[PDB]
Amino acid sequence: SRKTLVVTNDFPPRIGGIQSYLRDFIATQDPESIVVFASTQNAEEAHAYDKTLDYEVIRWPRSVMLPTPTTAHAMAEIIREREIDNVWFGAAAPLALMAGTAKQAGASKVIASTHGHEVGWSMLPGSRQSLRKIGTEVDVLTYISQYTLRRFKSAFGSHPTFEHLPSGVDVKRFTPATPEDKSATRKKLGFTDTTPVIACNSRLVPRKGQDSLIKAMPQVIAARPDAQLLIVGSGRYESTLRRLATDVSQNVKFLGRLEYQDMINTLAAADIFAMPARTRGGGLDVEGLGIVYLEAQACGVPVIAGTSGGAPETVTPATGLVVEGSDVDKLSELLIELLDDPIRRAAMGAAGRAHVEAEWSWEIMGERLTNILQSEPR
């Protein structure tokens, strides 16, 4: 059994995408084979959280962990003292620059995780050479999607192996609603069993395409006058969305950021999950993990996904439809068609559930990580 040190600037109790990603992947592993070396944003909250866990977390008493000589030496000391076999950098850039030190300290395998923003036109000076350095010293680079892999090109060079490691989804928490619960959820929203419901769970930013959905609504309600769009989440773009929703305000609900279970109940009672993510910000504002699509499929709800980044990779033609987010006419058409086709929706939702069970659960994804951490070095 190989022992892994996870070196990361991103770790709970701080909330975020990489925090959730690492927290959940670590949880799939044998706790005796895991040590975490993490930065500390709040020392009292960090300590309280670490007490709940069954594996060691060593806190670096800095808000930000940086690849300095003293951080390198501190890491090296942990590698020697805890007899570490693997060093897994939670984010490749910049911390995986300490990979050389990790190996000198006794680690026989270095893994580094990418998240999709390492390569782009806003890259800082020195960054391309850093990615090369990281590449030569890292044995396994994990990547979240085929899209990101393509975007890297040969930035990391010829040494590392690339392993696909997207997020899993908790298929026990996200689960299809019973008819009774679905009816009760709808009643609490002020709807009935026949109300056409489109749900969108996501941060309220232009990228997620809540604006596209709102703009499609006039056409959708012309076909289905009682159709309801549920916008679940919070973010800077809220006031724009509300402005955009003015002339369809009776058919669009802003539910705010909902409590976890309430959000699941709402998602599971919907007819369609729709998030037509589009790529913006000169190509730099792109969809990464697409977790909301996985959650929807786990709840047995048909999905409308955008063409942005790795979003299409989370669905199959059997579970969802991919749409160009900026094509509002095509979006409303797709929405109307699916709302008029309950038989297909039931089949798409059923296929959605089967798809996440077979390829997206934390049990399935956990196996991939176990292989990376427990295999002999190349």
Image: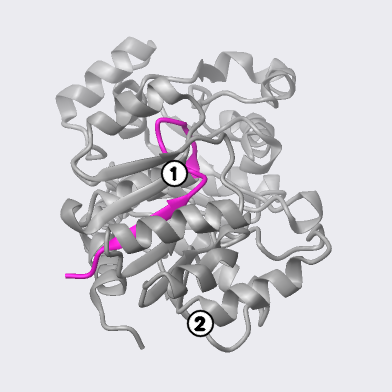
Q: Mark 2 belongs to which amino acid?
A: Pro
In the rendered view, would you say 99 is above or below 207?
Answer: below
Q: According to the image, label 2 marks what residue? A: 160
Using residue 24 as the reference point, say whether residue 357 is left or right of it.
left
Q: Is residue 200 visible?
A: yes
- Range of magenta residues: 1-17
Looking at the rendered structure, the kind of residue marked 1 is: Ala
Q: Which quarter of the image is occupied by the C terminus?
A: bottom left
Q: Quadrant of residue 196?
A: top left
Q: In the image shown, does 283 or 200 lie closer to the viewer?
A: 283
- SS class, disc 2: loop
| Picture quarter with the N terminus | bottom left
The foreground one among 205 and 108 is 108
Picture residue at 23% right of the left edge, 66% below the top = 367
At horizontal 58% and vertical 68% (from top left) the residue drawn is 147
Which mark, by number, is residue 38? 1
Q: Is residue 83 left or right of residue 112?
A: left
Q: Is residue 339 visible?
A: no
**The stretch drawn in magenta includes residue 4:** yes
Q: Which mark is residue 313?
A: none
Identify the mark nearer the N-term, 1 or 2. 1
Q: Nearer the viewer, residue 112 or 228?
A: 112
Disc 2 residue crowd, few under 14, some 14–19, many 20+, Cα 10 Å: some
Label 1 vs label 2: CA separation? 24 Å
Q: Residue at x 53, y 18 (%)?
A: 253
**Location of residue 186 (image quadrant):** top left
Q: What is the x, y in percent for residue 317?
A: 42, 65
- Residue 362 among magenta residues: no
Residue 200, position as x, y percentages in the image: 50, 34
Determine the main secondary structure of the stretch shown in magenta. loop
Label tally: 2
